[PDB]
Length: 280
Ligand SMILES: Nc1ncnc2c1ncn2[C@@H]1O[C@H](COP(=O)(O)OP(=O)(O)O)[C@@H](O)[C@H]1O
Image (tube, rainbow, N blue to C red; front, side, top):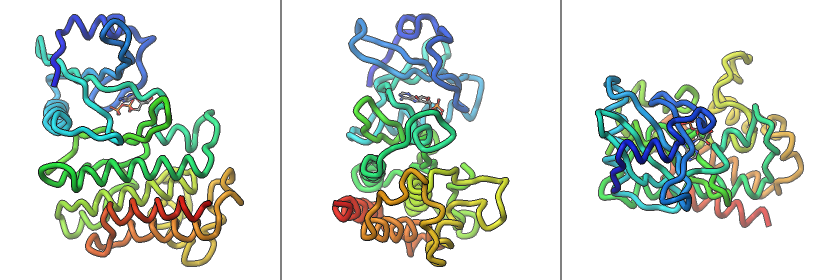
């Protein structure tokens, strides 16, 4: 893992110019930059060292990512804690979050096959977290803003601040059984799947009661045989019946009330790849 002088971080971000701000997370602000004389594009996150929350997420992010390498996880390039700073340096994800291509956006809507391929990519990254590291990594904040898209639309999981060995995505079983299970990622990922299909927030607190939480509303509509009616209008008629059925049954299994009933990410990944094949 690389360490950057605080001067190199200023050079990368044209001295934290707000032209280069991409957004602000609860850790701090994120800047687009370039290092190595402009060959490598980067996203740079500045935390606040006097936030106890921030410092915990900072070391968690560095402890995790410095040992992981996977096509569908955002790579951490390096970091800077010089001058009592908290700076993280990642690969730039040129197409932003999955969420900003699903709704509340002026970006074009995504073809079904690319939506499916984005969800397979994320499922591969999550599968690697659960089976490819020394111990299972529980991401704990899987959501559509934490799936980033690079210049070639490769889906990548990000935001490892709450990782251990958001409303609407929270495993309801946590508030009841109180354990740490990777099945809590499966639950959140199932909500992500329903988001890709229906193109609406996982939690819309303005709706009728049954519809507030996508995780409950979409299973309910599928049982009633009306899931077709809350599908993204851009997707109407674009999904074959066998892909629709396989995709929806896979999402449904992920948001079961009990984590032990839920499939593994391996099983989920295989069923999405099966769905993609049934789409052709
Ligand atoms: N690694 C990254 N590469 C590219 N853009 C990123 C990266 N991390 C965050 N962003 C940008 O930030 C936004 C989504 O994440 P954001 O909420 O801003 O930061 P965080 O992920 O820390 O909460 C998008 O506009 C996205 O382009």
